[PDB]
Amino acid sequence: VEGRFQLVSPYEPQGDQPQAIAKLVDGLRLGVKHQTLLGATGTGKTFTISNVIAQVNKPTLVIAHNKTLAGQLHSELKEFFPHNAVEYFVSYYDYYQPEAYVPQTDTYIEKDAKINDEIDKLRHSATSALFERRDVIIVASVSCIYGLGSPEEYRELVVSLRVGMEIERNALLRRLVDIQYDRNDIDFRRGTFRVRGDVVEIFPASRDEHCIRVEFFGDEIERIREVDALTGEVLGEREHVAIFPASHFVTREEKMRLAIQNIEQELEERLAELRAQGKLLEAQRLEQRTRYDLEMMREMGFCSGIENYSRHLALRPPGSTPYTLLDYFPDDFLIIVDESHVTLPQLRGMYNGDRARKQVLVDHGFRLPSALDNRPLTFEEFEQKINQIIYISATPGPYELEHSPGVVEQIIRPTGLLDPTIDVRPTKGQIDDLIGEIHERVERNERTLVTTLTKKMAEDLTDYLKEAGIKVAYLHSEIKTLERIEIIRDLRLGKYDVLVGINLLREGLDIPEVSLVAILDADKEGFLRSERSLIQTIGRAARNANGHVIMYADTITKSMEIAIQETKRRRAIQEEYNRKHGIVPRTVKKEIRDV
Amino acid sequence: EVDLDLVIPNDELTLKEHAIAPWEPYYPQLLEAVCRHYGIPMDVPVKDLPKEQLDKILYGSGGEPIYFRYTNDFGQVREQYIAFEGVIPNVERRYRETSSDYIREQMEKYMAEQPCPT
Amino acid sequence: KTLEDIRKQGYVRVRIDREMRELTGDIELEKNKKHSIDVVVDRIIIKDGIAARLADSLETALKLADGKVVVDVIGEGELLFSEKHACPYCGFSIGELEPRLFSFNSPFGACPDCDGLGAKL
Amino acid sequence: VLYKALAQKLHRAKAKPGEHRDIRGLEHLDKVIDIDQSPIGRTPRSNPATYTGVFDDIRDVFASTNEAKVRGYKKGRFSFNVKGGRCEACHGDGIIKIEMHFLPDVYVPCEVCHGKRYNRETLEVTYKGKNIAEVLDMTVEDALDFFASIPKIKRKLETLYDVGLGYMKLGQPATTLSGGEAQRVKLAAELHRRSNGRTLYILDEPTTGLHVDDIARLLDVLHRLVDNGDTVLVIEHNLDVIKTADYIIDLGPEGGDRGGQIVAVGTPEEVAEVKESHTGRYLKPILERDRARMQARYEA
Ligand SMILES: [Zn+2]
Ligand SMILES: [Zn+2]
C-alpha cells in the first residue's frame, strides 16, 4: 500500500480548469513525453497542476527560475498538500557566490560562505524524502541540475538500523563518522551526534526538531525513539531507522583509495604540463592546494570543496555527464517547469557560465582540469534525463511549442475576469495623454503601471509625473529585494498612484488595484517588446475588472500584432464563458501584508 | 601617586570624545555635570582651556556643591547634591580604599612612582 | 527541577531510593522524604581494548555529578572515585601532602586556635 | 623616546614617552613593531608553538581526525591549558616546579604524565603515527617536514626556520628560552606579513647568542624585510652587522654624562672617517679588511 497525495483545497476546479486537468492527466497516462499548459495569468495554474499530480501519484520535481517564485510555489504546494512531503531544494546559488578568479585584479573569490543551515537542511530533507516515501513534491531552482554525488553511494552507505541487531556502540559511532557526522554534546545541532555513555542521540541532516535516539543493553540495540531536541519529549517509537549521509559527496574506502591515486596522477600530469609551458607560479599554487586536499582525504576521507573531485571519487571517465538531483528521483518521475519561457533558457545558460568560471580557475592553477567535470548539465543531458514533462506558461517559448502536441488551453478565470482591452496611440504627446488617463484612474481610486524602454526615459518620466502632481514611485532596475515589497505594498495602499519601471515581468507586480498599464516604445527593438514579453506585460491589467492597456507606438510591429490578436481572442472566449454562465467580472480582493 | 601626564594621553584631545583616559566607559555624565556647572565647554582641545576650568575638573570644587543628575545603567534618574572631589583625588581615593588586586591594578595604570618627599 | 533535565538531555537509566527506574515513567518523589538518585550512564563487559569506552563513560558520569562517580561492581561491592584530595560524601579536602603540612613552625601546618603552640596558658 | 612616542601616536599606546620636543615624518609609516628581547611567556604554558599561533591550528587537525570524531574531542580536548584532556596532576604544566631556597628553582618532570603534558586517553588519538605530545616534542625542522601537508602550519613553521632556530622543539617552555631565542621567536611572528612598505621594526641586539655564520642568515632575513619597503632599526655593538647597515647613527663620545649627543651620522664609511667616533675608529679597519678579502677572492 502506497502513500498517496491528498489534495486539500477549499474550492473545486472551475472555468476551463476541469478540461485542462482531464487533458494533462490523460496525456500523462497515455504516455506523452512533452506537454504544454498555456495558462493565462489569473487562472489557478498551481492548482490545476496540483490536480494533475494528485491524480497521477508520481514523485514530482517542479522547477522555478528564482528564489521568490520557488518560495511561493513551496508555500502553495505545502498548503495544497499538508499531509505530503513538500520539499525545498535550492543551493548556494540562491544568494551566495561560487568559487571564482579574476585574472585582472588578481583576486581568488573563495567558496567560503558557510553552507547556510536552513538551505542545507532542506536539501537533505528533499533527497532523503526521495528515498523514504512516495508522496514527495520537490520545488527547486535551476540548481537541480548541479553536480551532485552518486545516488547508489548515497544509498548503500546508509546505516540501516533495526531493533535488536548484532551491533556495537563504538562501531556505530565510527560508522556515523564515516558518513560525515560530528560529535557535539556541548552544542546539539543538525548533523550532529551526542554520546552519553549508553545514550546515543543522532541529529539527521534532514530534520528540524525531530532527532533519533538509540541505545544498548549489551551488544544489541534495545529501543529507538524520536525525541524533540533539547527537550527529551518522546514523540516516536520506530523499530527500523535509516540514517543517511550528512553530505552528498561521501565515498567508499576502497573507491576512495583508488580515486586518490588517480588524483595524484592527474596532478602530476597537469603539473608537468604547467612547468613545461613556463607556468611555474600556477604549478606552485596547484601543488600546494591539491596536496593539502589530498592529505585531508587520505586522513578522513573528505575535505572542503570535495565537490571539485566528484568525478574522480565516482571513478568515472573524464568528461562524464555528472549525476544530479534528477537521478535521485525514481525512473517514472514527473517534471513541471513553471514560467517555462524563461526557466528553460536559464537552464540552458547554466553550463556556459559555470564552465567559464571554472576554466579560469584551471588556467591559473586553482583547480585540476577534472573540476570541469563537476558541473551543471548541458541542455541535452537534461533532455535525455526526462521521463515525462509539462511546461507551464502564459506565453510558451519556441522549444515548448515545438516538442509538444499543440497546447492545452486554460483561459477562463474563476472570477470571470477578462483579458484587458488594448489601445495603441501615437508617440507625439504621449506624456500628457498618459497623464490625463492617470488622472482619470486616480479619480476612480485605481492604480497604473508604466513601462519604458530605457532607464533615462523612466527617470525623466517620473520627474514629469511628480510635477503634474501625481503620486509616482520609481522601481529602480536594481533595488533592494525587501524594498520592492515595500514600494509595491505602498502602491496597493495608495501612497503611490502610479509605478514606473523598465521590467514589469519581475514578480510581485500582480496587483488587483492596477487597472491601467502603459507601454511606451511598444514598437522598439528589445527583449521586453517581444510577442511573449508583450503578452506577459498585458497580463498585468487582467487582475482588475476595468483593466486596460495603452501601448505608445508609431508603427505596428509583428510582436504587437500577435499580442493584441491573442489578447483579443482570449477576451472574446472569456466573455463567451461569462455570458454562458451569467458571470459578472469583479476584482479579486486581497489583504495587504506587513512585517 | 597619580601622574597628570597619564590621565591625559595628549594635551589636545576632544573632551567630548573622552580626553581624560581614566573616566572612560556614570563618570561621562559627571563630566557633563561639572562642565555644565562651571561653564566648561564640551567640544574642546584641552590645550586651549583656561587653567581654572582645568583646575576645577582635575582638583575639585573645594567644598562647593555641584548639581549632578544621572541615568543609571537601568534607566531610572537619580539626582544628587554632591561636593565634587575631582578626577585626581578620585583615582587616589578609589585606589587607596579597595583591597582588591584587580581594582588596584586598574587604577595603578594611571599612577607613577614619585620620590619620598620626607 | 532535576528529573526533567536529565530527561531534557535525554538520559533513560537512573537509580532512585535504591530502586532503579525508567525516565519518562512519570516519576514523582515525596517532598518530606529523602531520595537517593544515582544515574546509570554506561554498562560494560570486561574485554580487550575496552579503555576508550570506559574512559568516555567515566568522563560523562564525573561531569554529571561534579567529579563524583559510583562504580557498582556485580558480584562484589561498590567502588567510588572523585579525583583530587577530597571526600566523596562531605566535601572536606586536604589538597596535597607536603612536609610543611605537618610542621608547627609554619601556617601550612599550625593549629588555628593556638597558632602551632600546642600549649594554652 | 622614539618607540614610545611612535606607539602612543600610531597605536594609541599609553606608555609615557621620554622627554622630547617633537617627532616628524610620522605620516611615513603605519605601524612600529619593537621586537623585544624580553621572554615570550612567564609560565611553561607558553612556547614557540603557542606564541606563533601554530599550536592553535595544530589542535584543529587532531580535532578533525577519525578517532577524535568518534571520540568527540575538539580543539579543546587537545588544548594545553584545558581540563578536558591535560594531565590533571600537573594541571597541564607537564613540569612541576620544585622549591629551591637559596639555589634557583628547578623544574622536575610530572611523575604522572612523565612530562607528556596530557592524560593517557588524550594521547591515544593519533595523527600520521604520532600523538599531540609527540608532535609537541618535535623539532621545528622535523615539524615543517612533518607538516609539509598543511600549508597554513607550514608557512608559520617556515618563519621559525628562516629566523635562525629550527633546532628547538615546539613545546619547549618559554621560561627556558634564551633572551636572543625569545627575540627571535618574536622575529618569527613579525617575519611573514603582507608589508605595505610603511612599517618600522626595532630590534635590540638581535646578535645576542648567535654565531657569525648565524648573523649572516639573520641579516639575510632583515635585509629582506628592508627590501620589501619596510625600515629596520637596530641597536648593536656587533661590527659585522654595523658594517652591513646602509646608515648608522653613532651616539655619545664616552658614556655617562660624558655623552648623550650625536658623534656621527651617515653611511658606515662616512662614520668610519670620523676620528671622534670610537665606533668608526673600530669599524674603519674592518671595512678595509673585508674589502681586501673580497678583492682577493674576486681576482682569483
Ligand atoms: Zn593547638
Ligand atoms: Zn601532570
Image (cartoon, coloured by chain):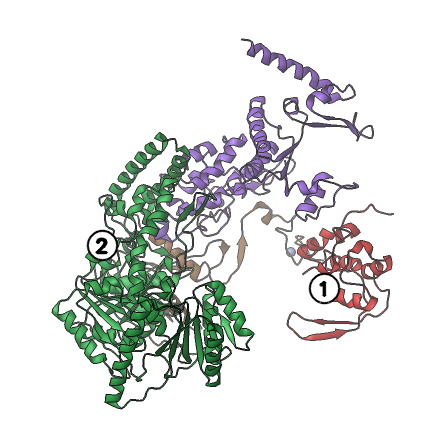
Chain colours: A green, B red, C brown, D purple
Which residue sits furthest left? A30
Numbered disc 2: secondary structure: helix
C28 vs C16, nearest the viewer: C28
CA–CA distance in space, label 1 to label 2: 71 Å
Quadrant position of the N terminus of chain A in the picture: bottom left
Say if A529 sits above or below A291 in the image. Answer: below
The lab-note entry on whether marks 1 and 2 share a chain reads no
The location of residue C93, given as percent across then percent down, is: 53, 57
Which residue sits furthest top? D300
Amino acid residing under circle 1: Pro
Q: Is residue D78 left or right of residue B11?
A: left
Amino acid residing under circle 2: Glu
The residue at the point 83 percent across, 66 percent down is: B38
The residue at the point 86 percent across, 67 percent down is: B63
D115 vs A507, nearest the viewer: A507
Q: Is residue A523 left or right of residue A148?
A: right
Q: What residue is pinned by disc 2?
A: A380
D148 vs D135, nearest the viewer: D148
Q: What residue is pinned by disc 1?
A: B28
Q: Which image quadrant shows ligand 1?
A: bottom right
